[PDB]
Image 1 (cartoon, rainbow, N blue to C red):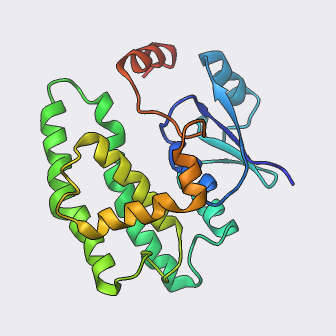
Image 2: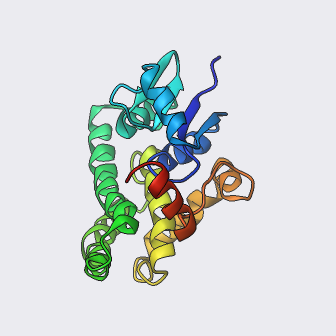
Length: 221
């Protein structure tokens, strides 16, 4: 069948959570990297970006845009979205909290230099007092290896991905959350995830200053 094709910059950005989910699901995919404003213009002018933005993923005959639409489809297609409407409600609640926190961290590099320190301190405060306690509480409530249904779901993948980003920010933030640490280890040892974390996979590195200032001028943000 058609192999999914991921259109995005050669960077983490708003495509990385899709790379994680597909890799975790054991699904082969291809990437088509946007290297210039001309590359992006061609996708727009040819009509393949509904809202003139990437990410865009070609899958099952669709040219899907909007990260949440892409992830929702992939999760359902590969049975990572729970078994019933109520499990999806828990999954959605969990992963939307993850996306809120992930959004903050995703946009810190583009923070005005004078608002940087305050923004970072707020992110760390919410991690220690709001989000990490919330997910530790879920894991402690049922004591099982997975967030929902005693079965791997997108929620485990999205959360562990975020845990790696929180580690990059500050290794100490997770220190008082032993169940989150255990989740990170177990999920990282799943064969598909273990391979994705090893070198040479589609997993992308953190944005460096040299690469940011480059695409910053090339793509007008």
